[PDB]
Image: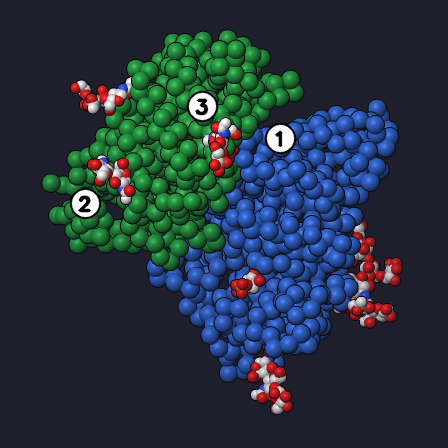
Chain colours: A green, B blue
Amino acid sequence: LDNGLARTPTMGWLHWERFMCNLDCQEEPDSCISEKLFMEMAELMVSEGWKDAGYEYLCIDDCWMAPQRDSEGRLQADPQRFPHGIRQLANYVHSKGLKLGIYADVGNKTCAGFPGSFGYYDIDAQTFADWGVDLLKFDGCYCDSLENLADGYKHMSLALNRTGRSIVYSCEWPLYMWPFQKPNYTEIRQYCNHWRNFADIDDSWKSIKSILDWTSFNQERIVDVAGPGGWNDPDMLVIGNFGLSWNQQVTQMALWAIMAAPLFMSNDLRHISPQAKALLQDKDVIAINQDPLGKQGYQLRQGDNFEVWERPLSGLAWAVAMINRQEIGGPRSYTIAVASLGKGVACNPACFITQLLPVKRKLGFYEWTSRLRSHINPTGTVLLQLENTM
Amino acid sequence: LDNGLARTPTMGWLHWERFMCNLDCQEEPDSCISEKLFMEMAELMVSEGWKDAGYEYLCIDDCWMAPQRDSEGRLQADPQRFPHGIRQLANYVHSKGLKLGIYADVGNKTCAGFPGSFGYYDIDAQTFADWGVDLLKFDGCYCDSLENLADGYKHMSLALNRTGRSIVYSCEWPLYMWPFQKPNYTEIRQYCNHWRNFADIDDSWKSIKSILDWTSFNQERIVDVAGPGGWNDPDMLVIGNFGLSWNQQVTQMALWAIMAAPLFMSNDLRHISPQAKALLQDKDVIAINQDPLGKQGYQLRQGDNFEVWERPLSGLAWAVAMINRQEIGGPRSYTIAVASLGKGVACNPACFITQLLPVKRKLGFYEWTSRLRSHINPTGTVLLQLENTMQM
Ligand SMILES: *[C@@H]1O[C@H](CO)[C@@H](O[C@@H]2O[C@H](CO)[C@@H](O[C@@H]3O[C@H](CO[C@H]4O[C@H](CO)[C@@H](O)[C@H](O)[C@@H]4O)[C@@H](O)[C@H](O[C@H]4O[C@H](CO)[C@@H](O)[C@H](O)[C@@H]4O[C@H]4O[C@H](CO)[C@@H](O)[C@H](O)[C@@H]4O)[C@@H]3O)[C@H](O)[C@H]2NC(C)=O)[C@H](O)[C@H]1NC(C)=O
Ligand SMILES: *[C@@H]1O[C@H](CO)[C@@H](O[C@@H]2O[C@H](CO)[C@@H](O[C@@H]3O[C@H](CO)[C@@H](O)[C@H](O)[C@@H]3O)[C@H](O)[C@H]2NC(C)=O)[C@H](O)[C@H]1NC(C)=O
Ligand SMILES: *[C@@H]1O[C@H](CO)[C@@H](O[C@@H]2O[C@H](CO)[C@@H](O[C@@H]3O[C@H](CO)[C@@H](O)[C@H](O)[C@@H]3O)[C@H](O)[C@H]2NC(C)=O)[C@H](O)[C@H]1NC(C)=O
Ligand SMILES: *[C@@H]1O[C@H](CO)[C@@H](O[C@@H]2O[C@H](CO)[C@@H](O[C@@H]3O[C@H](CO)[C@@H](O)[C@H](O)[C@@H]3O)[C@H](O)[C@H]2NC(C)=O)[C@H](O)[C@H]1NC(C)=O
Ligand SMILES: *[C@@H]1O[C@H](CO)[C@@H](O[C@@H]2O[C@H](CO)[C@@H](O)[C@H](O)[C@H]2NC(C)=O)[C@H](O)[C@H]1NC(C)=O
Ligand SMILES: *[C@@H]1O[C@H](CO)[C@@H](O[C@@H]2O[C@H](CO)[C@@H](O)[C@H](O)[C@H]2NC(C)=O)[C@H](O)[C@H]1NC(C)=O
Ligand SMILES: *[C@H]1[C@H](O)[C@@H](O)[C@@H](O)[C@@H](CO)[C@@H]1OS(=O)(=O)O
Ligand SMILES: *[C@H]1[C@H](O)[C@@H](O)[C@@H](O)[C@@H](CO)[C@@H]1OS(=O)(=O)O
């Protein structure tokens, strides 16, 4: 989407995976979908170094809406859970130097069953613009035809543009289409800053493996369309929650960097281990995700329960990720000719290799003739940066 | 098995899940199955508090053997990887205050393809005894028929007995029967100090879920046969490795205590986080696993991706485990009438409740009529100890 936004993949925080549709503010005031939750996260994004590391969009997912539109036909914030309303929440988030994301649905209801935007695309767009919203995530539920799905995603895209406000447009057009026909990604990119391809992430290693496996299977169709203003969205970072080992968290952070994914944390910034925080705030790894060239990486190889992925970077650098998919035993040895990496140019005539994950370690100078040898933890990833000597 | 051993579930370390059948000492020396791996593991069991906590048995799994029996038809330690032999490793292990486990197979070859024990039960049993072996793990690969399987396990049991050495006998008889017919656990219990029921664990939450789901589904068949001298074996603790979140690790330790499981760590004691170490050495959870009453716990309730397990302990005390099987969102609230726990006994007329996992927290006096309110992490477990009391 040529709106001048998402020139690098969008970074921030989204409530869905961790906080879901929790409407019980009486029995659970700290966990419920409320403006207090979003203000708490806004304060911590400033105070705990998130904004400084580049996490900039504080995003509301589903279940923020009143059950009905107003007399004037507009979407409303739940009067109890969002009593000051979205415009006022946007004002607070802006005062902290952050941006606000909100959620709507292309169909007749949101997925969780609140007002759909079908019939209301123009008003909803102008409502969001008036409220000071900086990002829209547009989910795909309760849409009766591919025709309505396409027209809706395009119509909301054009309606956002016409408001005159810079609003990042996050689409789920491919995801909701894929069961019925192959999406046209060239067309999707013309209308969307990023697009969900695949099933919702959850707090599990199974979920991460299924996202990587879908992405490597479909890479011919999706890798080349990605670039400044338009990204494949493999869904939220779940680092800092309950379901992932350290090595599985490292795999998610490393491969979300290789894939030039939007980095939307869905965690509790009030309760996050130092280790999870330092991984998510990892400057070198965010610098890979945020590389201004914006060329999506890809799977180079798969065999013997190993994966090699690589991403071309600015200035003749490459990122290389090596995944151990064997979930038994100890750190497993993998070796690859450096001449096989970055299409033959990364290490011709030589490259300096730095390991970034699981720990930062200079590995030294590798000649074009060299083999890189590494031990990779089960369900873990080794992330390397290659700098060509020339 | 009435050999006076395994009156509580056996505790120790077994190499299999973490080191497997790594024979490449040239290119993977730190991972390979060698005497030096076992010697170094023995030193760390002493120096890093493992023996103190109850982990007493240092056990060799498959791939210790020479490819062939000697001229006198006895088994041989691999000459390159075990050049000083089992006898001397047994001496080293005994010198540190620990006991040595070894492995063999009821059939013609070990599962990894080394010399099987069929035709040699008596000589192999005497070999282990002369060697100073304190435990045998006996896999089921390469067995012709149920008659051979059953005949072998029964044979090796009496063979080990006929040596007059105390040797914990660890059988996979049930596990290698399931593809043919349902096991008879009273027979198995007569011959074996513990028995593998289900497929090998690996370093994954999927593996843990699969072992717990098989256990709860099958609990009426297996829970009551367990007791001092004979235990259900749900396979090794894999805490300290790579595949489990903190919450999934707490779930394994909590539920292995509930199930009166033998506790065989399969990890690298040279490279283990303080957090995994503190969980595996947790005195209060080991004390549940090792409760002298020795009655195996069970799943009380399932529904809404929650599980409630409980285990009766000596002295009218109960352990209660609450598992959140929802792999999304945040900590979920679960409430239950204390009356519904410990068959209504635990908290009649009151109990004192101590949370043990994920952290140790005195919760206080609960009257028989009162409710217990908890919050359980996704893939995590809250483990509680209920002490029957007359106070409050
Ligand atoms: C080869 O196979 C045979 C059986 O096939 C096996 O022999 C059996 O060995 C076991 C284990 O030692 C024997 O069990 C012990 O039996 C003695 C004697 O029991 C009889 O006589 C007593 C006299 O006191 C009577 O009261 C009783 O009713 C019996 O008729 C008992 O003294 C032993 O009990 C102690 O240990 C038990 C655990 O095994 C406890 O349950 C019990 O409470 C006892 O106390 C324990 O804890 C105490 C804590 O203070 C501690 O102080 C004690 O020292 C002890 O640890 C036990 O029941 C069984 O009798 C043998 N059976 C037969 C048929 O001979 C061989 O052992 C086996 N050989 C090898 C090497 O594998
Ligand atoms: C509404 O849709 C139009 C059509 O794409 C958007 O126009 C495009 O806007 C971008 C971003 O401003 C333009 O590129 C930029 O040009 C400026 C000024 O020269 C430059 O400084 C930037 O570095 C960048 O190259 C882009 O050329 C332009 N396209 C067209 C056809 O005019 C517009 O941004 C959208 N507006 C909103 C509110 O979304
Ligand atoms: C949101 O809900 C509305 C109202 O239920 C949907 O409008 C209805 O959509 C159906 C298509 O499935 C239309 O039915 C068609 O009508 C013609 C006759 O005019 C008939 O030949 C077709 O076979 C079919 O039955 C229906 O006319 C239409 N109703 C109105 C009031 O417009 C709407 O499509 C839903 N939107 C999404 C995105 O699901
Ligand atoms: C380990 O391998 C040995 C060598 O193959 C096995 O010994 C064999 O045992 C089988 C019984 O399952 C014997 O088969 C029978 O042979 C007789 C005729 O000799 C026939 O009447 C029967 O109908 C049946 O075919 C076999 O004879 C015997 N060995 C040899 C060399 O003939 C042994 O069973 C294996 N052990 C285990 C525990 O699996
Ligand atoms: C996929 O979608 C794209 C964009 O809508 C289509 O490409 C356009 O096709 C028309 C007719 O060939 C051209 O006028 C435009 O130049 C194209 N736009 C761009 C930027 O390429 C393409 O036709 C669609 N492909 C398929 C197979 O349907
Ligand atoms: C399982 O095996 C055990 C032990 O071999 C059997 O126990 C026998 O039970 C009968 C009574 O039905 C006793 O009279 C015997 O003395 C017991 N022992 C033996 C060695 O036979 C048990 O019956 C078997 N269970 C089933 C259902 O087959
Ligand atoms: C649509 C999105 O795919 C998901 O990320 C989230 O925004 C919810 C909101 O309701 C919805 O997915 S769901 O699978 O229908 O819950
Ligand atoms: C048999 C046991 O079940 C397992 O724990 C281990 O001891 C190996 C030894 O080779 C074997 O299982 S396997 O699935 O055949 O590897």
State how far apart marks 3 and 2 are (Cα).
Answer: 52 Å
- Are callouts 3 and 2 both on one chain? yes
Please give the residue where the numbered disc 1 appears in the rendered image: B332
- Asked if the beta carbon under badge 2 is closer than 8 A to the nearest atom of ligand 2, the reply is no
> Mark 3 touching mark 2, by CB under 8 A?
no
Provide residue B200's location: percent of width, then percent of height. 57, 58
Label 3 neighbour load within 10 Å: few <14, some 14-19, many 20+ = few
Image-quadrant location for residue A257 = top left
Image-quadrant location for residue B380 = top right
**Which amino acid is tagged 2?**
Ala
**Secondary structure category for the residue under label 3:** loop
Does residue A346 sit above or below A283 in this rendering? below
Provide residue B126's location: percent of width, then percent of height. 63, 74
Residue B160 relative to residue A73: left or right: right
Please give the residue where the numbered disc 3 appears in the rendered image: A119
- Are callouts 3 and 1 both on one chain? no
Disc 3 vs disc 1: which is toward the camera?
3
Residue located 37% across and 58% down the image: A304
Residue located 36% across and 26% down the image: A155
Disc 2 vs disc 1: which is toward the camera?
1
- Asked if the beta carbon under badge 3 is closer than 8 A to the nearest atom of ligand 3, the reply is yes
Question: Of residues B298 and B11, which is closer to you in this image?
Answer: B298
Label 2 neighbour load within 10 Å: few <14, some 14-19, many 20+ = many
Question: Of residues A87 and B358, which is closer to you in this image?
Answer: A87
**Secondary structure category for the residue under label 2:** loop
Provide residue B362's location: percent of width, then percent of height. 70, 27
**Which amino acid is tagged 3?**
Gly
Of pointers 3 and 2, the one earlier in the residue sequence: 3
**Secondary structure category for the residue under label 1:** strand
Please give the residue where the numbered disc 2 appears in the rendered image: A346
